[PDB]
Length: 286
Image 1 (cartoon, rainbow, N blue to C red):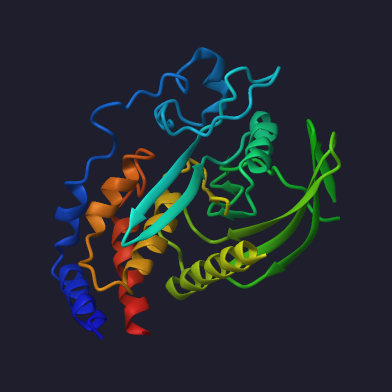
Image 2: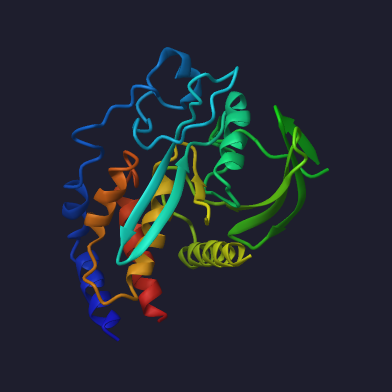
């Protein structure tokens, strides 16, 4: 029940408004070896949603080079953290563009991805935040050598689960990909329903566990920019796992480690304070 001491500390820090000082001291990106030269190539300009939100060279997801994409470039970062003995493996990526759908599915295939955690809407405020890279039911699409079929979509209130089949058109191999989309989460803000977000995290945790039981692949997390709401998901799941290991909690240490793998994770104070609220409620129900 040492979680009780953690929950008081967290509630007090939030209640007294000491969260901000902690958050604003965390650097947004690497100080050194922060080169994003491949991402900055003129040839890759159309592949970035924002020319300043970029993967670092040494952790970018490298696609096998193709005719259409010689550098095999996608705006996506490997995120590998070890926190309290747990080795976490994610890929964090931006929302696909019309012209990066083949790249996105090539990454899904090559990296062995079984679960997509989508935490953006397709459209918000009249703007595209993610291209519709998977088919709409009523049910198949082809991007280069990958055929994607939507089997079903089931709504769980705050999020929806879509069963996808992905087929390699040159080998005939097929794989199931589970698409878990949180549907009401404004960009730069927080989920509307805190408990709904916890149930979304619970479903990601469950499906990862059970698909692993049947080299485990990274979880693919994406938003629009691939840093804000993506960062909330990753930092929340890591910190929740920390709650069982007695070791002293150090959220800004963890977020700093994460931003060493992909810049700008967790864009706003409300997103960071939301992670505190998530942990408090998780501990309040333990």
